[PDB]
Image: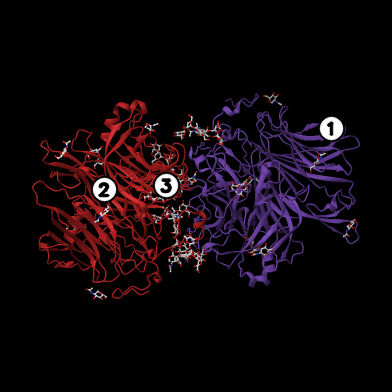
Chain colours: A red, B purple
Amino acid sequence: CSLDQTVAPGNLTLCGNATLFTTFRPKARFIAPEGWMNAPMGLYQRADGSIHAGYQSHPKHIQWGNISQGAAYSSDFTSWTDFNGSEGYKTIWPSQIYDIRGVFDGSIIKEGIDGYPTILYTSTSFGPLGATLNEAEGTETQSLAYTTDDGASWIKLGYGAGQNPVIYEWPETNLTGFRDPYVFQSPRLEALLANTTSITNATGDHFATISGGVHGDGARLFLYRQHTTGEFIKWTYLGPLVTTGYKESYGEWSGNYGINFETAGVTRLNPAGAAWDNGSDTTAVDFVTFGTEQGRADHQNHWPLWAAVDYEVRDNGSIEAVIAYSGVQDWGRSYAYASFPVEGYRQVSVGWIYEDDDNVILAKQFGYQGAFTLFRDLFVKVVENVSPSTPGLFEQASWSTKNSTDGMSVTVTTLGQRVVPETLAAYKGNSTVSTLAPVMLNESAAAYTPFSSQPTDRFYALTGSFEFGLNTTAKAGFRVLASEEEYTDIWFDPASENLTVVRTASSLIKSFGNDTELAKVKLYEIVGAESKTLNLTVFVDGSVIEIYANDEVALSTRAYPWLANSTGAGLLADGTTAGDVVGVSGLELWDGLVDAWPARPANTSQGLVWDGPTAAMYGLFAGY
Amino acid sequence: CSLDQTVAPGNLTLCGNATLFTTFRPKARFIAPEGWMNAPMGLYQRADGSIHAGYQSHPKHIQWGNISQGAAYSSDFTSWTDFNGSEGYKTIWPSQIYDIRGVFDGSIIKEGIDGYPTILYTSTSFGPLGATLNEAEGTETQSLAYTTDDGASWIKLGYGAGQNPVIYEWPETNLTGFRDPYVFQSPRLEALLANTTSITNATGDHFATISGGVHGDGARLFLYRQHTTGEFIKWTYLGPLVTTGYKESYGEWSGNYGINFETAGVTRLNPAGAAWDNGSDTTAVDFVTFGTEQGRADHQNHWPLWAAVDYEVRDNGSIEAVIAYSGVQDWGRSYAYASFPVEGYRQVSVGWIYEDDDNVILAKQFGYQGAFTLFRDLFVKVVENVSPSTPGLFEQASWSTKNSTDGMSVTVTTLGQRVVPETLAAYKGNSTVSTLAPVMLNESAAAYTPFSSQPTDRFYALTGSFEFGLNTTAKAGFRVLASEEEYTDIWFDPASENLTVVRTASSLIKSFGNDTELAKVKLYEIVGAESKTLNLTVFVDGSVIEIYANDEVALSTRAYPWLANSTGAGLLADGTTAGDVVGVSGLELWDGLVDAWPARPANTSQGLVWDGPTAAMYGLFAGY
Ligand SMILES: *[C@@H]1O[C@H](CO)[C@@H](O[C@@H]2O[C@H](CO)[C@@H](O[C@@H]3O[C@H](CO[C@H]4O[C@H](CO[C@H]5O[C@H](CO)[C@@H](O)[C@H](O)[C@@H]5O[C@H]5O[C@H](CO)[C@@H](O)[C@H](O)[C@@H]5O)[C@@H](O)[C@H](O[C@H]5O[C@H](CO)[C@@H](O)[C@H](O)[C@@H]5O)[C@@H]4O)[C@@H](O)[C@H](O[C@H]4O[C@H](CO)[C@@H](O)[C@H](O)[C@@H]4O[C@H]4O[C@H](CO)[C@@H](O)[C@H](O)[C@@H]4O[C@H]4O[C@H](CO)[C@@H](O)[C@H](O)[C@@H]4O)[C@@H]3O)[C@H](O)[C@H]2NC(C)=O)[C@H](O)[C@H]1NC(C)=O
Ligand SMILES: *[C@@H]1O[C@H](CO)[C@@H](O[C@@H]2O[C@H](CO)[C@@H](O[C@@H]3O[C@H](CO[C@H]4O[C@H](CO[C@H]5O[C@H](CO)[C@@H](O)[C@H](O)[C@@H]5O[C@H]5O[C@H](CO)[C@@H](O)[C@H](O)[C@@H]5O)[C@@H](O)[C@H](O[C@H]5O[C@H](CO)[C@@H](O)[C@H](O)[C@@H]5O)[C@@H]4O)[C@@H](O)[C@H](O[C@H]4O[C@H](CO)[C@@H](O)[C@H](O)[C@@H]4O[C@H]4O[C@H](CO)[C@@H](O)[C@H](O)[C@@H]4O[C@H]4O[C@H](CO)[C@@H](O)[C@H](O)[C@@H]4O)[C@@H]3O)[C@H](O)[C@H]2NC(C)=O)[C@H](O)[C@H]1NC(C)=O
Ligand SMILES: *[C@@H]1O[C@H](CO)[C@@H](O[C@@H]2O[C@H](CO)[C@@H](O[C@@H]3O[C@H](CO[C@H]4O[C@H](CO)[C@@H](O)[C@H](O[C@H]5O[C@H](CO)[C@@H](O)[C@H](O)[C@@H]5O)[C@@H]4O)[C@@H](O)[C@H](O[C@H]4O[C@H](CO)[C@@H](O)[C@H](O)[C@@H]4O[C@H]4O[C@H](CO)[C@@H](O)[C@H](O)[C@@H]4O)[C@@H]3O)[C@H](O)[C@H]2NC(C)=O)[C@H](O)[C@H]1NC(C)=O
Ligand SMILES: *[C@@H]1O[C@H](CO)[C@@H](O[C@@H]2O[C@H](CO)[C@@H](O[C@@H]3O[C@H](CO[C@H]4O[C@H](CO)[C@@H](O)[C@H](O[C@H]5O[C@H](CO)[C@@H](O)[C@H](O)[C@@H]5O)[C@@H]4O)[C@@H](O)[C@H](O[C@H]4O[C@H](CO)[C@@H](O)[C@H](O)[C@@H]4O[C@H]4O[C@H](CO)[C@@H](O)[C@H](O)[C@@H]4O)[C@@H]3O)[C@H](O)[C@H]2NC(C)=O)[C@H](O)[C@H]1NC(C)=O
Ligand SMILES: OC[C@H]1O[C@@](CO)(O[C@H]2O[C@H](CO)[C@@H](O)[C@H](O)[C@H]2O)[C@@H](O)[C@@H]1O
Ligand SMILES: OC[C@H]1O[C@@](CO)(O[C@H]2O[C@H](CO)[C@@H](O)[C@H](O)[C@H]2O)[C@@H](O)[C@@H]1O
Ligand SMILES: OC[C@H]1O[C@@](CO)(O[C@H]2O[C@H](CO)[C@@H](O)[C@H](O)[C@H]2O)[C@@H](O)[C@@H]1O
Ligand SMILES: OC[C@H]1O[C@@](CO)(O[C@H]2O[C@H](CO)[C@@H](O)[C@H](O)[C@H]2O)[C@@H](O)[C@@H]1O
Ligand SMILES: *[C@@H]1O[C@H](CO)[C@@H](O)[C@H](O)[C@H]1NC(C)=O
Ligand SMILES: *[C@@H]1O[C@H](CO)[C@@H](O)[C@H](O)[C@H]1NC(C)=O
Ligand SMILES: *[C@@H]1O[C@H](CO)[C@@H](O)[C@H](O)[C@H]1NC(C)=O
Ligand SMILES: *[C@@H]1O[C@H](CO)[C@@H](O)[C@H](O)[C@H]1NC(C)=O
Ligand SMILES: *[C@@H]1O[C@H](CO)[C@@H](O)[C@H](O)[C@H]1NC(C)=O
Ligand SMILES: *[C@@H]1O[C@H](CO)[C@@H](O)[C@H](O)[C@H]1NC(C)=O
Ligand SMILES: *[C@@H]1O[C@H](CO)[C@@H](O)[C@H](O)[C@H]1NC(C)=O
Ligand SMILES: *[C@@H]1O[C@H](CO)[C@@H](O)[C@H](O)[C@H]1NC(C)=O
Ligand SMILES: *[C@@H]1O[C@H](CO)[C@@H](O)[C@H](O)[C@H]1NC(C)=O
Ligand SMILES: *[C@@H]1O[C@H](CO)[C@@H](O)[C@H](O)[C@H]1NC(C)=O
């Protein structure tokens, strides 16, 4: 095993465990110290204003298993510190018959048991578990734990009658899944159900959804309500909140609803951020965010989706969330988005970016798998004065339209997503910032034009506004992680409405994924404008490439170039002519970003271990 | 629920939990503070000379489940003190994927991990488990833990490759069971295998048996040897030590070998006690003690047996233990005998006495189930100058015979068992002792003759020597726990060689067992004697009746008389005439015995709990 990054890569499968630990590793984002991570969990803003973030964790392994909560905290979403206790950076782990198979995703009741922050989580035990298997009741249940030390440790309720697990009965038969409880307060839902509480007797101020589905008959999000305020054992099943069909799709802008939901959450937003009104704010919109399984040919069969919903009250004192329009939260290699409230009327969302090594060829050599996305403020994106001649506008696919009285303009409403400003400020302020001169891309434009300033490593951000003619057939974007032999091309093609990431040349290492990523982006044309604009922000962080368009569209992906000098960046142009011109302005390079884990040394590997021959006997975890 | 013990019992199933806690409860023996117990485990003499005793335990329940090690200690086998830690009187409990289904029986390596006492125990996980079920590999494995604080707590080795569990591969396919590791040193076995260690490479100073069997083909005791002295991870399978047939029986004196072994141990004894020679002591005998399953119509399908064995060395460097003769360790409601070495060349054995409430009618009202037997010294019983005309003598069923050179007398050899002298001394010294005048039972004898002194409660011992004519047809023995309406009759009938406990009148409460207990007792007739003698010792301790004959035969059983005055005792006589006389001498009553748990209050119940609806979902434990 040679680690010479000035020559072509050898056979890297001969390299030892964690020998490639720093080679492709993100530095500017949330990631475990080592080993396996997946879904964010247990997210809450603590009493001191800091953010507690948990995550599904399997230390000293590079596949999933013994799944536990790892945790850390931050005062600004950006610079983090690990918890360190008797189990290292873990704070909840399998320990009881009811959760021994894994401590799955959970969410926080901020004033819970004895007034302490309390997690409701999926506690798993033995038996077939999965949407394509024949799971039985009891394999997935829901349990409580609380913390008296602000998340350094958690105390589980005892096992037994009237204690853990607190939710165990399946609400319908033949579930595909029964997990990922999302606890939330909702003046909106309380107002809607206030006339029906005699029917159900459930009058608590907390609701909880549980994600799943029914075999052969599509996904389900099940709604529960806390039975009595200030009491946390009894949760009353109201009914299905969201019901979708077996592999139903709302269309090209909306992914596919698959067979089973995961990590679903419920929020209410307005143009400024989170909305906590009872229905009285006419600018507020109810949203559900959710993952779907088995409705996708690639990306681990996983779509992270969202839908705007209109709530209807059923006669049995339950709620139907009728989907009004439906979109995609991220179009790339990310999943398991969790959202949580943050003071100042914010709802903040973060997901998990998996690697692109699905055959597990270099995972041991990495010594880790996975990272988070950046933390994102959610809000209602409102575009005013939209031209009715915007192509495809009245499809109303992942947005809504409201005509002006005179019919000459439209107001467009959709889900907005933008990187939390704390992170943008810290990134910019800690970087070497190069403000770049505008560039007109015309007949003289090369295919690739390097920026006048270049990055110095694999940790940078780019911003640009691309102004296109209304009938352009030109393409433009950014090339990143670029040398002559390796590069990753981010293209937007207004004629097809497709944002793509072409990765055929991303790396000389052939075992990594190289498929083309794709997102749909609607450029809403403004009344009286003779052009249309794409605002693109791109973060390059080790192997992560995370793309944001117009505070709306997100696409996370991976690139693993071998060569030390595959760090360059610049502009891409295709079909730009004297007459079909692309004006690029607002160009900025931020070189360096932030060291997100200042207390950690560069190499936080502790080695990898094998569970031994019993792993195959038990059949629950891969074992490595 | 009335607790009036001066009138007939009402419907006691209406009584609350633990309302009958003290009513039938032993006071003078090892018993858990409350709840469920079964097999002794983890027995060893500590560095300070005290005895550590563990037991299979399920606190606050009255059926088996979450099976854990409860523990206590004693300096004299007799007066005990509970450990008290973070889990009360438990010291090992289910906590890892490999043992979450139960911490089953285990035994002690005295100088183990880092020089500390170390337990090798059966760690159980999910799946069908049982001799009549289709168990698979991995469900039962063997794991290590060690103590740095003399048994107050135990630290398990980590889960994984080269750590726990340390034995997981089945030595043959289709096992009926794979548990109860018994670790022991043996100069005998080391000497026998010394010429074969090249074949196996196993040269350690510890051996371990694991108890089981093969479906359809009888029980098996599997022998392992520690691979290297001072190292405790690697244990090498040598071969089957004991192989018996599917429900094979050696005869009327030997129970039945069933389909599966449990709690098996290996020892070597001589007339004085434990023998630690390499084979050079010609008075020493190799013994195996073991439980069998599914070879008995009653007594929970369980026989606690023993066999004298002759070891043969196989060509593959393993040992066959050929059964020379075979007996019964206890003929009544006891099982799961464990033996352990004690300083002064002793081997001490103790078992578990279950209740006689197999339909679980009053278990909740008790608030506990189970106790230990008394602790017993094992030795080789040798009877010299035995008459060749002793009936059935050359059957050599559970004994061996050696003729004198002239053929006029025989030396008989069998397993001896006697209550440890520490307990006999303490019992006698703390009791009110009444030495009773001898009684000739003849034509004038009533059926029942009360002793001249009577017990004052349900805690007493009786001794007597019954001298019978060589051709008697008379019966005699002891009645205990006796009033006019309730009593338990212990009879010996020399003509049939049967010791019986008749329990048709033991209690007015009809839900308890009332079947007749039976043991075979061989009165070895001495050359020149014109009579034959039965030395009977009986312990009455709450509901326990524990009978010892001639330091050889043991029979433990249960009686639950309701009436407060059903405490009396005396002599039984049947068919005694002027010519067929039974001379009773050495009669002594010890009233009171010892308070075995002086620190415990009378009622150590902490209530009972239910595991809730998930107990049936998981399907592992009853839940109560
Ligand atoms: C199979 O058997 C298993 C083993 O038995 C069993 O698991 C065990 O289950 C039991 C019962 O559910 C659990 O017991 C609970 O423990 C909770 C605390 O748990 C935390 O702390 C313990 C112990 O703490 C110490 O010991 C460890 C180990 O040495 C040290 O690390 C610590 O530093 C600490 O040491 C100090 O204290 C020691 C003595 O205790 C000293 O020796 C020492 O010197 C130190 O000073 C830990 O062991 C726990 O760790 C385990 O669990 C965590 C997850 O929780 C894991 O991460 C970890 O790996 C371990 O597995 C843990 O950290 C108790 O809170 C709980 O007590 C209450 O509940 C019951 C009711 O259910 C009540 O009886 C009792 O009164 C308590 O409730 C009161 O208090 C709470 C708030 O504090 C109130 O909400 C409640 O209403 C009530 O209030 C009362 O008082 C008020 C007045 O103040 C009054 O106003 C109220 O009205 C009311 O009266 C309970 O004891 C036990 O932890 C499990 N153990 C393990 C190892 O798993 C398993 O379930 C079984 N399985 C099956 C299938 O049956
Ligand atoms: C799923 O995830 C699960 C959770 O991660 C996982 O279970 C965990 O597995 C790990 C790894 O196997 C276990 O870690 C081991 O822990 C052993 C000690 O265990 C005992 O102590 C711990 C911790 O102790 C404290 O914390 C608790 C909780 O707060 C307190 O109650 C205590 O008071 C104590 O607190 C003090 O210390 C704290 C910090 O640690 C402070 O915060 C605090 O202020 C106090 O000061 C307990 O948690 C354990 O309890 C659990 O387990 C018991 C059974 O064991 C249960 O009954 C109980 O309910 C709990 O479940 C327990 O009591 C360590 O000994 C062990 O460390 C060694 O082994 C590894 C190799 O495997 C080495 O890396 C390491 O060096 C250690 O080995 C050295 O030491 C030993 C002798 O001491 C030598 O034999 C050895 O050779 C070596 O010697 C070295 O040093 C020598 C020089 O001195 C040198 O000469 C030698 O050459 C050599 O270098 C390991 O850390 C962990 O306990 C599990 N946790 C739980 C909760 O289960 C599970 O397996 C996962 N499942 C799957 C399927 O993957
Ligand atoms: C005295 O000790 C006991 C512990 O032994 C304490 O706890 C009680 O324990 C018993 C079991 O011994 C439990 O009985 C079982 O109850 C099941 C239904 O329970 C529900 O209804 C009752 C009645 O109002 C409620 O009290 C329960 O509420 C509690 O539990 C829920 C969780 O479900 C919590 O949310 C609450 O907060 C409470 O904690 C329940 O809502 C019942 O199904 C079960 O069924 C069988 O057993 C009986 C008797 O043998 C049969 O008649 C019946 O046919 C069922 O038999 C089964 O038997 C075999 C083998 O098991 C199976 O193969 C069959 O298919 C069949 O299913 C049983 O009756 C009791 O619920 C529980 N009480 C609790 C926790 O409060 C007592 O509390 C304690 N008392 C005191 C004063 O301390
Ligand atoms: C680097 O990290 C790893 C952790 O990832 C550390 O531990 C090693 O981990 C790997 C797995 O990543 C283990 O590989 C597996 O080994 C199995 C056979 O092992 C035995 O032989 C080896 C070789 O001499 C010994 O080292 C082992 O000894 C250790 O374990 C025993 C317990 O058994 C202990 O007693 C010892 O003390 C040691 O701790 C063993 O004796 C092997 O069966 C297993 O098989 C598959 O995997 C490969 C690769 O994918 C395939 O070629 C093969 O076909 C098998 O594939 C399976 O794949 C699928 C899915 O799993 C199944 O469906 C198939 O049916 C099929 O079974 C694998 O190769 C390795 O043993 C282990 N080493 C240890 C513990 O020492 C490294 O130590 C660490 N390195 C350093 C320097 O720190
Ligand atoms: O770590 C479990 C956690 O991850 C999610 C989201 O991806 O589920 C994954 O893990 C399950 C258990 O292996 C799989 O069945 C599932 O297909 C997979 O997506 C959460 O739903 C869960 O809490
Ligand atoms: O934030 C104002 C308002 O919202 C409520 C809704 O019941 O609480 C939400 O907002 C808090 C601040 O972000 C969160 O801590 C809380 O978890 C969330 O439910 C009100 O309590 C509050 O007055
Ligand atoms: O507590 C388990 C312990 O008891 C024994 C001896 O009786 O086994 C009993 O428990 C097993 C598990 O429920 C049963 O399969 C078995 O039939 C029963 O005798 C020990 O062998 C075991 O270690
Ligand atoms: O007891 C004398 C002699 O026996 C050995 C056998 O190797 O140890 C046994 O006896 C000890 C005392 O009862 C026990 O502690 C020990 O566990 C048992 O193997 C010798 O070590 C000792 O010299
Ligand atoms: C980058 O490195 C490779 C190999 O060292 C080299 O061929 C190339 O010229 C270098 N510089 C570039 C592409 O600017
Ligand atoms: C309420 O009605 C809906 C629609 O019929 C149904 O799915 C749900 O199960 C009902 N709730 C109950 C039975 O609690
Ligand atoms: C919205 O405006 C477009 C263009 O003016 C028109 O085609 C459509 O009918 C209008 N819809 C409504 C509801 O008025
Ligand atoms: C650098 O980053 C840190 C950590 O997020 C942040 O607190 C600090 O303000 C940043 N420095 C700037 C903006 O100059
Ligand atoms: C653009 O995207 C869609 C997928 O939504 C695809 O079917 C179409 O072929 C793409 N067109 C071009 C020109 O890339
Ligand atoms: C024992 O008690 C019962 C009921 O109180 C009574 O009938 C009997 O006479 C008492 N005394 C005896 C049997 O000596
Ligand atoms: C040794 O021989 C015996 C008798 O053939 C056999 O049962 C045992 O399995 C053998 N040991 C091995 C293969 O280790
Ligand atoms: C043992 O003694 C009896 C009676 O003297 C006799 O029947 C038998 O043959 C003797 N056995 C041997 C081996 O001498
Ligand atoms: C009473 O019993 C205790 C506890 O076993 C014992 O130590 C003491 O010697 C006994 N008293 C006597 C024999 O007088
Ligand atoms: C004595 O015991 C045996 C069982 O070993 C039995 O078959 C026989 O009938 C009994 N005989 C008498 C008279 O009790």
- Residue A514: % across, % down: 32, 62
- Look at the numbered disc 3 and give the secondary structure of its residue: loop
Mark 2 nearby-residue class (10 Å; few <14, some 14–19, many ≥20): some
Mark 2: amino acid: Trp
Residue B85: % across, % down: 48, 48
Q: Residues within 10 Å of mark 3 (few under 14, many from 20)?
A: many
Residue A199 image point, x, y percent = 36, 26
Question: According to the image, label 1 marks what residue?
Answer: B445
Query: Residue B48 falls in which quadrant of the image?
Result: bottom right
Q: Which label was assigned to residue B69?
A: none
> Spatial distance from mark 3 to mark 2, Cα to Cα?
25 Å
Quadrant holding the N terminus of chain B:
top right
Q: Quadrant of residue A275?
A: top left
Residue identified by numbered label 3? A131
Q: Does label 3 point to a residue whose CB lies under 8 Å from ligand 5?
A: yes
Give ligand 11's quarter of the image. top left
Q: Amino acid at mark 3?
A: Ala
